[PDB]
Figure 1 (tube, each protein chain N blue to C red):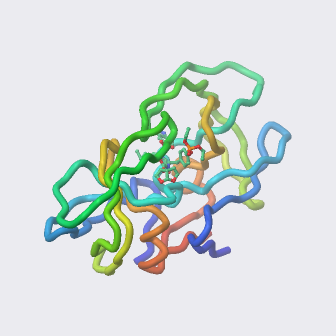
Figure 2 (cartoon, helix red, strand yellow; figure 1 turned 90 degrees about the vertical axis):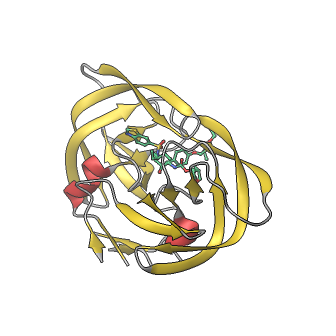
Amino acid sequence: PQITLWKRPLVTIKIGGQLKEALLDTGADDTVLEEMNLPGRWKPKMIGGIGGFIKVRQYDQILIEICGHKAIGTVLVGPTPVNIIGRNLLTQIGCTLNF
Amino acid sequence: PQITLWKRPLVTIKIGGQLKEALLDTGADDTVLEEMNLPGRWKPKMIGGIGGFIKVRQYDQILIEICGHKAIGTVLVGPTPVNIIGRNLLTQIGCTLNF
Ligand SMILES: CCOP(=O)(COc1ccc(C[C@H](NC(=O)O[C@H]2CO[C@H]3OCC[C@H]32)[C@H](O)CN(CC(CC)CC)S(=O)(=O)c2ccc3ncsc3c2)cc1)OCC
């Protein structure tokens, strides 16, 4: 579809067998999701933005479905205030900016 | 144009007569630029991101040209890790997400 930017671009995603709301975020290199107890191994990581860094758990080869579009890649889990879909997955669903 | 997301969506902007590079950021409500001298009045504001809140200077009704497209609106100035163009100006230049 086409998403205007008057409001936050929030969509439904499916991950680890759960549905959630997440921001389609062209300023996010990586995908960062709210605390959730995903199975499997993970690597510690720190990601930075406005205000500083947070500590997150990096899980690899995670399947996420975004508005029916499937994607698989790296997902970071940590105390983010919002579920964020970053470019690593946005590219995979064919998402572009257009003006 | 149509901008893909394999790399960061960086563009040249012109503000207060100066050229700079900035990130088109659909996850940003507001536009935040690194410390710089802008003419006119400003008021202190706080904004929050992934790592907490920072103090910024709020400039209203500022002219800014984004990849050839003119906007006039609110620009925050402060210790952001990178210059970001948020939805308040993305809307003005007619930017949408498409997949
Ligand atoms: C409301 C909940 O609480 P809250 O008020 C704000 O919550 C939010 C927290 C984060 C966002 C998303 C964030 N937007 C943001 O900073 O926007 C500011 C400006 O406009 C306002 O609108 C929303 C907030 C205000 C960017 O889109 C993405 N970021 C990178 C950019 C940093 C400038 C480029 C470096 S990233 O997230 O840091 C990030 C993501 C993946 C990644 N992979 C490797 S690095 C790395 C870094 C949106 C809302 O904060 C109090 C705790």
